[PDB]
Amino acid sequence: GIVEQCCTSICSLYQLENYCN
Amino acid sequence: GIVEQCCTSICSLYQLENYCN
Amino acid sequence: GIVEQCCTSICSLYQLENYCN
Amino acid sequence: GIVEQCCTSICSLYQLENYCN
Amino acid sequence: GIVEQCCTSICSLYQLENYCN
Amino acid sequence: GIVEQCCTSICSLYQLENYCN
Amino acid sequence: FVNQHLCGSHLVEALYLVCGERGFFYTPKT
Amino acid sequence: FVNQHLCGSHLVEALYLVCGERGFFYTPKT
Amino acid sequence: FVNQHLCGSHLVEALYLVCGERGFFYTPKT
Amino acid sequence: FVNQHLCGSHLVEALYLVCGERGFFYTPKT
Amino acid sequence: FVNQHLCGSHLVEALYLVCGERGFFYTPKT
Amino acid sequence: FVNQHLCGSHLVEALYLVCGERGFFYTPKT
Ligand SMILES: [Zn+2]
Ligand SMILES: [Zn+2]
């Protein structure tokens, strides 16, 4: 998931925004 | 809420666990 | 300046990009 | 010691508490 | 103390070294 | 540069000070 | 023996510390 | 914005900043 | 939907997040 | 509480939160 | 040319920075 | 002062503390 992707690869702020309430 | 319990007031680390999944 | 825009006032992450090189 | 254990292995909050004053 | 010297008042990084072991 | 040196090797606070304005 | 205030990023650092792999929610408007 | 390499608590910090007052969910794999 | 205040080390953490490899300047006296 | 993997300054952050007003000692191996 | 205030977790981050391997004590009640 | 091993946002934190009100430039290699 996002936690793993951001650490093992890279992720964008736009991907992170999907986890906002 | 979390802000009112822990920022505005004070809370323990045990109370913080109330917000775990 | 940055402090006046973002600390004293508030700014968005988009405005923060004004201070990138 | 605790600094090394927490980094090379894992440690608990209860182990950390032994370093409080 | 450290809080009074550095939080309530201000201190330099040199003064912070007073609290090293 | 300094960003890479501090991460792949070590760096001093005195080296960092060269990046202050 | 009494607690301190935890606000903003310091509050979510604390949530990460106590919850870790369990995950958490930070919902300040609640 | 630039892409990100975020582990541990640094991911939490980033979520805090992106989401602001909306808050967020932190959901690692178990 | 409204923004928060970012000050001191939290402000430069935010600059690092949004600028990354581009680099940035933090010049509070400006 | 969950177990922790803490290096560098992250261990200091954790000690701060656990200990609160008691304060703490940070004593790495040399 | 003048210093700022360092409080709470920011103060122990600063202690970690300046002391590192030497270790330190954070004893706010003193 | 002690020598430092600083990656990522930790280098930014260190620059903030060293430089204070002078501010600083963060300039990674691209
Ligand atoms: Zn803070
Ligand atoms: Zn880190």
Image (cartoon, coloured by chain):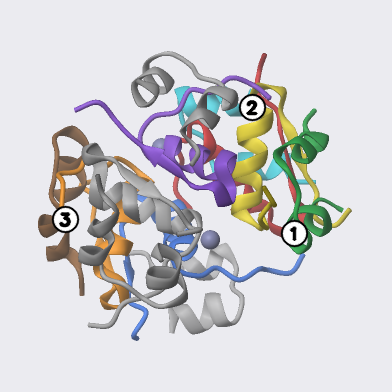
Chain colours: C green, D brown, F cyan, H purple, I yellow, J orange, K blue, L red
Secondary structure found at label 1 = helix
Q: Is residue F6 visible?
A: no
Type of residue at label 1?
Glu
Determine which residue is flagged by label 3.
D13
Q: Nearer the viewer, residue K23 or H6?
A: H6
What is the x, y in percent for residue J6?
26, 42
Q: CA distance from mark 1 to mark 3?
A: 36 Å
Q: CA distance from mark 1 to mark 2?
A: 22 Å
Q: Quadrant of residue H29?
A: top left
Query: On screen, H9 above or below J22?
Result: above
Q: Chain of mark 1?
A: L
Are labels 1 and 3 assigned to the same chain?
no
At x 25% / y 69%, what residue is drawn?
Answer: J19
> What crowding class fits label 1: few (fewer than 14 Cα within 10 Å), some (14-19), or many (20 or more)?
some
Secondary structure found at label 3 = helix
Type of residue at label 3?
Leu
Mark 1 in CB contact with mark 3 (< 8 angstroms): no
> What crowding class fits label 2: few (fewer than 14 Cα within 10 Å), some (14-19), or many (20 or more)?
many
- Ligand 2 near label 2 (Cβ, under 8 Å)? no
Are labels 3 and 2 assigned to the same chain?
no
Determine which residue is flagged by label 1.
L21
Q: Nearer the viewer, residue K6 or H2?
A: H2
